[PDB]
Image (cartoon, rainbow over all chains, first blue to last red; front, top):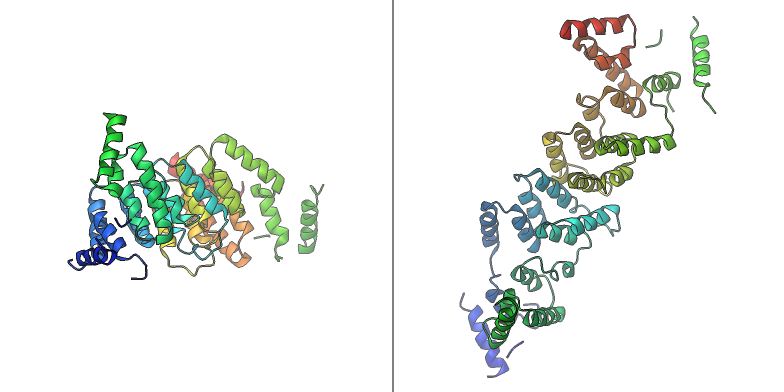
Length: 204
Length: 205
């Protein structure tokens, strides 16, 4: 949201990226990716996949692969897992790559929608809800997944016209609800102190 | 194999067919084999049998029979809304084939289906995955864990006569020496059936 001059703030934001376009506000997106911890490279993406897999969380690695758009990598990661249910889920996700050219409206899309509705694991629910009717607004609005991982796809795979609307709605939600994950948006600003005050009022 | 005139036995066998009437050359023998094996049932009675198998609780056998009779969307509908989540996952995997059968092959989805066919314990879903991953019946006709009556049904329904004769010869020569009691569908209660029962008595007492 910006805020001594506009060119002055633009150049001090630029010098942070010039320490370590395609959009009207590109350097702000880079700074928001730096703040949210979502400026990892492809080799860093593979390292994060390996680290997440090393804890036994295969579903989290598949969700991270889908979040960055590497759906065949999610197929590979959930393949050769330690669970038969995970292998069935991997086959279901693998039944999308040849399907992306289709207009849709299949009974398979209805099966994926029902499975995303009935599943208890939030990451697999994210995958099955994203694979059928492939839009990003069905993933970045639920509260089951972390707000950091939601901003990992809102700042990366979404445009600045609706990004300000999403950020405004999420900030207005977390200020009055008092969720500690709103500190992604507000930081430790005085608005962050207001968020913490609502958190103290709600939870002591 | 057949074996006093050929035309007279053919016409009385056609009369045998024309008893319950309320593109192959051997249609006066395939229909007799379907009568003998119990696979000359109507489609409404097929729906009734699907309801019966679903009411018995064997959803995997109902899915296998739907795959055998070809209505793969009905297999998806039967395996969906079942008592298990695993069956729903299998239904999603099965449904991932209808918009996929035009693909040339050697892709990761078919590799995953072949891996699932290799690893899974249920034989009905094993042959379901074997038929879904590759559209060939020969991985289904030689699976021993499924019943031989179903295999003969899907051999008389979908096979050329030059291949059905080889399948019948192979399966009969297997079940005569192996002593399998389900070879009596192929051989009948004949002297060769007595040879089958003699081998069964030798193996099992």
